[PDB]
Amino acid sequence: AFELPSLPYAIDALEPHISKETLEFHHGKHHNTYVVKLNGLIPGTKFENKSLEEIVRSSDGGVFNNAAQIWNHTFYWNSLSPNGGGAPTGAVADAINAKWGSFDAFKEALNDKAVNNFGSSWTWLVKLADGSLDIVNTSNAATPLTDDGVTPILTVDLWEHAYYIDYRNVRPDYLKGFWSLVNWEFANANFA
Amino acid sequence: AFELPSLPYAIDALEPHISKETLEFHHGKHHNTYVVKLNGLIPGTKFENKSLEEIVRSSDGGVFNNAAQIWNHTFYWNSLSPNGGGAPTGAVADAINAKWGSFDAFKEALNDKAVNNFGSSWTWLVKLADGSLDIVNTSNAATPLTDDGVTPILTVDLWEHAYYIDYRNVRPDYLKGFWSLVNWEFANANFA
Ligand SMILES: OC[C@H]1O[C@H](O[C@H]2O[C@H](CO)[C@@H](O)[C@H](O)[C@H]2O)[C@H](O)[C@@H](O)[C@@H]1O
Ligand SMILES: OC[C@H]1O[C@H](O[C@H]2O[C@H](CO)[C@@H](O)[C@H](O)[C@H]2O)[C@H](O)[C@@H](O)[C@@H]1O
Ligand SMILES: [Fe+3]
Ligand SMILES: [Fe+3]
């Protein structure tokens, strides 16, 4: 049924911010496992011939947890780039300034939401129905893809497997890696 | 102020099931952080002269997340022993037989509960008010200590930091390690 998307860059392209080993396990195993598990759940069911987004928005229990984790992870690989990092640009840079006054204040605000996102979770940059940006946290497999009026723009995966190999317990070190990789091209494509 | 209890065994005593490095991070860093955070939250609140258990049983939000995680980890360390593992003994071996028919059926049931416990979580062996055992799952910092009349007997921490260093994504390998360390003396003390 579903397939594991290719990573949008080479396996060592995010070094030294996220390691080759971390991509091998995180994409090659964790992401892959949600694809396998979902493909094992849907045969014969009403979800069999639906798209992944259709399934995320219409399921609960294990079908949701795997489908939403497939979507979220694909969204996360796209939120990183060997050519990202640095200051934001475009429409998204101006929208960050509009909501938080400055890029630096926005970074401080997302870092605080990310470090304190308790347990397995995701911290997101979203665009609300009034066109303004905000940061929201979700837990486990939950995702703003299911929230009316809310458009995902960027995400940071805070389940421990996302960073434990490279950073152990220090999420602030992982976030410094994320800011070095953040894909503003994908953020602007989503915003626009 | 609350303090981090000493580990009940040497830093390499659970090898090769759980490594010295995992104990250094899990106990010396993760467990410690919850102590530190809770002590920061307590002054100026209704929790200033309360025992850890009184706090776990009467709080929510951050005070609960940190207090319950402190209690949970302390109980987890006691649930492992360099002299544990193997077949259960005494009163707990018999209760396991009464509830599940056999130790192997119990072990299959717990593994199934643990491997499927989604996200950061804990799997528990508990004694119900009716005197029988059962297996229950909790998410993030939640714990059966808040369930009136339920008595915790053993737990296995399933947050990824508990096993990622040693086993990466393979929880069943981690669970084989747990079965080689399980502390039946603590299980029996708790049951009795
Ligand atoms: O797909 C299996 C089930 O996964 C979830 O339930 C598991 O994980 C929970 C914590 O996130 C535990 O409380 C629970 O005991 C586990 O079974 C999901 O919520 C269920 O609907 C799924 O069937
Ligand atoms: O102690 C800080 C807070 O921890 C929890 O809230 C954080 O973690 C949640 C996920 O478990 C996120 O959804 C939330 O956005 C974070 O702020 C707790 O629920 C709060 O009450 C605590 O104040
Ligand atoms: Fe992940
Ligand atoms: Fe833990």
Image: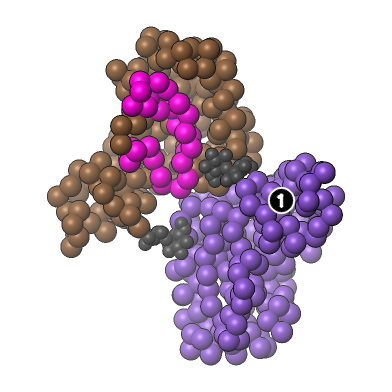
Chain colours: A purple, B brown
Residue A173 image position (x, y, % from top left): 51, 61
Residue B133 highlighted magenta (yes or no) = yes
* Left or right side of B83 for B53: left
Residue A187 image position (x, y, % from top left): 68, 77
The relative height of residue A90 versus residue A157 in the rendered view (above or below) is below
The relative height of residue A78 versus residue B5 in the rendered view (above or below) is below
* Left or right side of A190 for B12: left
Please state the chain letter of the residue tagged with numbered disc 1 in the rendered image: A
Q: Is residue A111 visible?
A: yes
Q: Is residue B20 visible?
A: no
For the residue marked with disc 1, what is the amino acid?
A: His
In the rendered picture of this protein, how many numbered marks are placed on residues? Answer: 1
The answer to whether the beta carbon of the residue marked 1 is less than 8 Å from any atom of ligand 3 is: yes
The relative height of residue B151 versus residue A80 in the rendered view (above or below) is above
Residue B162 highlighted magenta (yes or no) = no
Magenta segment range? Answer: B122-147
- The residue depicted at 50 percent of the width and 72 percent of the height is A110
- The residue depicted at 75 percent of the width and 61 percent of the height is A54
Assess disc 1: are there few (<14), some (14-19) or many (≥20) residues with their C-alpha within 10 Å of its C-alpha.
many
* Left or right side of B139 for A54: right
* Observer-nearest of A10 and B128: B128
Of the four image quadrants, the one with ligand 1 is: top right
- The residue depicted at 56 percent of the width and 33 percent of the height is B113
* Observer-nearest of A32 and B93: B93
- The residue depicted at 52 percent of the width and 65 percent of the height is A137
Residue B56 image position (x, y, % from top left): 29, 45
Residue A145 image position (x, y, % from top left): 65, 67
Check the picture and name the quadrant holding the C terminus of chain B. top left
- Which residue corresponds to mark 1? A31
- Can you tell which quarter of the image residue A116 is in? bottom left
- Can you tell which quarter of the image residue A79 is in? bottom right
Helix, strand or loop at label 1? It is: helix
